[PDB]
Structure formats: C-alpha cells, structure tokens
Amino acid sequence: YKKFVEARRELNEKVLSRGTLNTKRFFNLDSAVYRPGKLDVKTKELMGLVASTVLRCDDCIRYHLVRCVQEGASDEEIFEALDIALVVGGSIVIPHLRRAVGFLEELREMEKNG
Amino acid sequence: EYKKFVEARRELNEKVLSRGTLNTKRFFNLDSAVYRPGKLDVKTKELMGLVASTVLRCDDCIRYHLVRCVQEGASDEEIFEALDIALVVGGSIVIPHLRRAVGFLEELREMEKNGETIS
Amino acid sequence: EYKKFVEARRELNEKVLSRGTLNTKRFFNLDSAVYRPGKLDVKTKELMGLVASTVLRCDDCIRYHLVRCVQEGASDEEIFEALDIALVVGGSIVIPHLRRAVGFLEELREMEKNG
Amino acid sequence: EYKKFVEARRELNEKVLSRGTLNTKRFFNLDSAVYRPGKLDVKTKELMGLVASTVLRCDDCIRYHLVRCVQEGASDEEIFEALDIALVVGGSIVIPHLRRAVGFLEELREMEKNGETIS
Amino acid sequence: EYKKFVEARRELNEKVLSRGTLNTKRFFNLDSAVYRPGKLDVKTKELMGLVASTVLRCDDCIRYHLVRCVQEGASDEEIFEALDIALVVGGSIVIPHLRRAVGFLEELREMEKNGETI
Amino acid sequence: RRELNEKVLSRGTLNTKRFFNLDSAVYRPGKLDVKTKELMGLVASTVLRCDDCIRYHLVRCVQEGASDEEIFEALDIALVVGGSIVIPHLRRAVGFLEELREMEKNGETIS
C-alpha cells in the first residue's frame, strides 16, 4: 500500500522541486479540479476513477481509489463506476479493473484493523 | 446540428445491429444498461459517461452523453465541473472536443429554453 | 463518397511522400508490405488491419481496410465477426466508428451490385 | 512468468466478478464469447485478439491471447506476421511490448516442447 | 478552410471560456504558457507540440501547431523531419492525419507568399 | 532489454527489422539536430506513456547534451498535452533522470 504512498509524496515533491512554474501550476490544477463545487468530492473522485480506468493508469486508479474510500464511497459505488469505464474503455481495461479490485480490498482490510 | 445527430445514431445503430451479431446486440445493450440507476443516480452515471467520452475524445459519444446529462437535469455547472476533470486528466488534446461540446450544449440549452424536446 | 475517399487517399498520399523524406517513403512501404501474403493470407492480413484500425478509431484507415477485405473476398459475415472483437476490446467509444463502417460497407456491397 | 500470470488472472478475475455486478459479469462473458468459431476460424479470431491487444499495449491481454494462439495451433511465423501488423499500425511505442511477448511466446514453446500443459 | 478554422476556434474558445470555470481558464492559460521560449526556443516547443499532437492524432491541435511552427520560421524540412518521428512512434494510424497536415501546410505557405495574415 | 531486441529481430521478420531501422534512422541529425530529435522522442513517449521508450530517450537526451532545464521544458509540454494521467510516468522520469546525474557525475558510460 504505502509503498506507493511514499512513491507518490516523494516522487511528487522532486518533480515540483526540480520543476517549473508551469509544472507547479499544472499539479495545483490537477488537485484543484477535484475540490467540491456543484458536485461533491465523492462524485469527482469517482469521475477521476473512471477517467483513470479508461485511460489505464494503474497509479492514478490507485490514488483515486484511496480518495473515494476516504470520501466514503461504497464498494457498490466504486464498482458501479468501474462498470462504466469497463464498457466504454473495453476489455483491454480488465487487467486494470482486475488489479484495482485487489487494491480496494487491501484498502478495506485496514478499515477492520484501524 | 442536433437533429443531424440523434437521427444518424438511431439510423446507423439500427443498421449496425441488423447486419450485426447476437454479440453486437449484447454489447450495445450493455452500453445502455451500465448507465441505469443503482447506488449512484442516473445523472451521476451520465456525467461519468461524459468524463470517459471526453478523455477518450469521441465526439458522438460526447454528444450523446450531453443530451443524457441534460435530460437528467445536470446544470451547466455540473457538466463543466466534469468536463474540467476530463480536460485536466486527458490533457489539452481534449480541447478541440471541449469546444464542440460547448457549442452543442448551447444548442440543447436554447431548445430547452424554447420548451423543445430533446431525448 | 468512395472515389472522393480514394482519389484523396492516393493524392494526399504521393503528396505526403512528395514533400516527405526517405524515412517517410520507407515507412509507407512498410505499412503496405506487412499486409503481403505469408503464413497468413492477404485476407486474414487485411482483417487484422481492420481490427487494428477500429480499436484505434481511425475512420480513414478503417475505410481502407474495409474496402480491402471486400476485394479480398471477405463476407459481411466475416468482416462483422472481426468488428465484434474490435468492439469488445476497444469499448463503447468505438461504436460511432462502427456506425460509419457499416454505412460504408453496404455502400460497397451496393457498388459491386453494378461492378 | 506464465504460471503466475494464469494464476493471478484467474484469481483476480473471480475476485472482480465476485465483488461486481451482472454488468461486470455480462461484459466478461462477452469478452470470451466474441472469440468463438464463426464464418471465421478461432485461430483467426484469437490472432485478431493478439493484434488488438498489441496496438493497445496491454501486456496481460497480450500474454493471454498468446497462450490462446498457441493453444489453437498458430505457428510462431503466423504469430509474427500478426505482430508486425500491430507494430507497424501501432508505432514504435509498441516495441517494448513486442519484446515481452517474445520472451513469453518462447516460454510457452519450451513448455510445449517438454509436453507441459498450456491452458 | 483556414479563415473558417481560425474564426471558429477563436469564437469557440471564447465560448468555452465564458461558459467555463476558473479551472478551465487556468488550464487554457497553462496550455499557452508552456510553449513560451525558455531554455528551448519557441520553434522547438511548437514542433514538440506538433509531434505530441500528431502521435495523439488531434487534427485541430495539429493544424494549430502547424501555423505556429510556420509563423516561427520552421522550414517544411524541419516540420517533416519532426513528423517522421511522430509517424514511426505513433504508427501508421497517424498517416491519415499526416495527409491533412500536408495539404494544410502548403495552404499556409500560400497565404504568406502573399503576406496574408496568420 | 538491449538483448531482448535481439530476440525480437532474431525471431522477427524482414519487416520487423525494417521497422526497427526507421525507429533508429528517424532520430539522426538532419535539418533538426539530435538533441532536439531525442527531446521530441521524449515528448511523444511521454504523452503516449511508454516508460521503456521514455527511459531510453532520457539517456539519449542526457547523453546528447540536453540539460535537465531543457528536459523539463520538454516534459511540461508532454504533461499539458497528455494530461494528468502522465504524472505517474513524469515521476519515474524525474527519478530516472537524476539517477543519470548521480552517475554521469562519477564518470560513467551510457549505452
């Protein structure tokens, strides 16, 4: 799990560090686009999940899975979102869906310990 | 150009299935079923279809989920907040599609204004 | 429709190669060569291009491989079994490209109806 | 790796279906259904799966479709005639995937040479 | 097709902005900012935009970056050499776009031959 | 890797080899220079999200003169055009790059 929570924070820092003003603004924008608006954050994180799945980025999927849980999304919710990505995106996304499910249970197996 | 759209979809889709296969039909049915009501409401699922269609850059798909979002009563704000997510995730190549999507959405809003139907 | 496409094809074709490079010319040779007969026949070959073209959603490419499959003896029956795979693998986003392929396909099986 | 592939796939597959929905399930079924014999051979159907998964750069999809092409008696020569089509249509960004698919295709060939089960 | 392409993009762009969010403006600005001369001159940046837009197959982004390349003094040699890169990396699926980009390139060299605005 | 290309060309075809040629040719100096061409390969490879293609192009850039400054200016273009899904690959690119500066510094060849 946090093998990618540190692979994130850490590698994210460097990039912004040895970055550019433009790089910084993009990242700020990436994060900004999810903040609550006329749509709550749960919804936007699910859309992030959907877009990440159809575009097949395991790391983005992982990140958004985390946030969704954190935003109180149910597995029923997460999976109803993933079915959309699967159908629009095709069967090539199955290996990603396949790994996204495993990550999700690993996540829930922390909501039972602490 | 809205009437250009809705008509050609019903057209070719019919043709497609016609000379299609039982699989062609099963997939098409599935493309509709996945958007139906569940723990997530229909407006939420239709905006997600808008997000997927935009990052994957498919105009007709974008057009289709646009009317669907309208029907479900999504506010232009709601749509743009979703389109904002597609734009940032899929990059600026998505811009030419976001432009058309707005001209199209404006057309659907005019019709709604003049009480015209859009299904 | 058909000619507008082909005449434009070959025209913009030599035009690109025209102002193009040697690296260009070579590549176009490749795209056309890899479909040459081998342990797999030209039809099978061209139906794989059709599948490749559909999942990457390149209408123009699709149209090219589709006309090629017909002239290679493929049937709407076989062509469609190919598109079905393209559909499941590529996803719902390919449907708009499936529509156009069909409309263009019949327009073809409607031309050999006169030769 | 091959026996790690077929294991996780199978396991995570039943895992996705498990925690999923009738739509998930119906989609997967359709993913296998579209490869069954028709006016076109199953070897041809599977090689097409190989081409599509290659131009789209999906390693798991590639490995899976390789065992199927082998299981359906495709020869390394037939296989490469298909991959060269995916490599050309898909550009050089596919080349890295081509590398892996080769070290995998020969692991299977070596498996079958020692009469080992490839399913 | 030019005076039609530019006159629509400009209006569509304004339309997208006005009906858009602050996030949309910021993103559109960032998309502009990124091609400004830095350690890399703008001709190179625009050529990279053309290569990224070609392997990604966005016709509009292609026409757009092409004019930019031109108004930046890029020969048809530099432009093709960069296109060859997009071709090999992007695959033969880009060929259709490579065609349209050609017919458009010339249409641009035309307008300038006659000092026509770009 | 470098060896895998052998196994590929080896088990390959006349076309597999002809394609591998173009992919190498296309990047030699011409009206545009090598440094530029390689940064373009970095671009294309970043928007298309191929780590192997990115890494290879990073080495060539690093080994072709290009500085982190020029390399980041190239990456930002990829980030904006390709979008936020490239960020993970941006990460691994940055981490790889400084791994070549925490190496070329101590004088070391780069294939």
Image (tube, coloured by chain):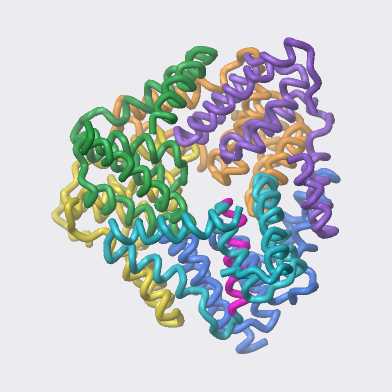
Chain colours: A green, B yellow, C blue, D cyan, E orange, F purple
Give the residue at the far top of this rendering. Answer: F105
Question: Could one spot residue C3 in this view of the protein?
Answer: no
Residue B12, position as x, y percentages in the image: 41, 72
Q: Is residue B34 left or right of residue B91?
A: left
**Splitting the image into 4 quarters, where does residue E108 fall?**
top right
**Residue drawn at point x = 23 percent, y = 40 percent:** A43
**Residue drawn at point x = 63 percent, y = 49 percent:** E97
Q: How many marks?
A: 0
The residue closer to the viewer here, B43 or E45, is B43
D44 magenta-colored: yes
The residue closer to the viewer here, A22 or A108, is A108
Q: Is residue F26 left or right of residue D118?
A: right
Give the residue at the far bottom of this rendering. Answer: C113
**Image quadrant containing the C terminus of chain D:** bottom right
Q: Is residue E33 above or below residue B105?
A: above
**Residue drawn at point x = 46 percent, y = 61 percent:** C94
Residue E106, position as x, y percentages in the image: 71, 41
**Splitting the image into 4 quarters, where does residue A46 fall?**
top left
Tell me the chief SS of the magenta region.
helix
**Residue drawn at point x = 61 percent, y = 29 percent:** E68
The residue closer to the viewer here, D5 or F5, is D5
**Splitting the image into 4 quarters, where does residue B25 fall?**
bottom left
Residue A70, position as x, y percentages in the image: 24, 33
Residue B71, position as x, y percentages in the image: 19, 55
Q: Is residue B115 above or below residue A35?
A: below
C36 magenta-colored: no
The residue closer to the viewer here, B50 or F108, is F108
Give the residue at the far left of this rendering. Answer: B115
Q: Is residue F7 left or right of residue B24?
A: right
Question: Could one spot residue F73 in this view of the protein?
Answer: yes
Question: Which stretch is magenta?
Answer: D42-57
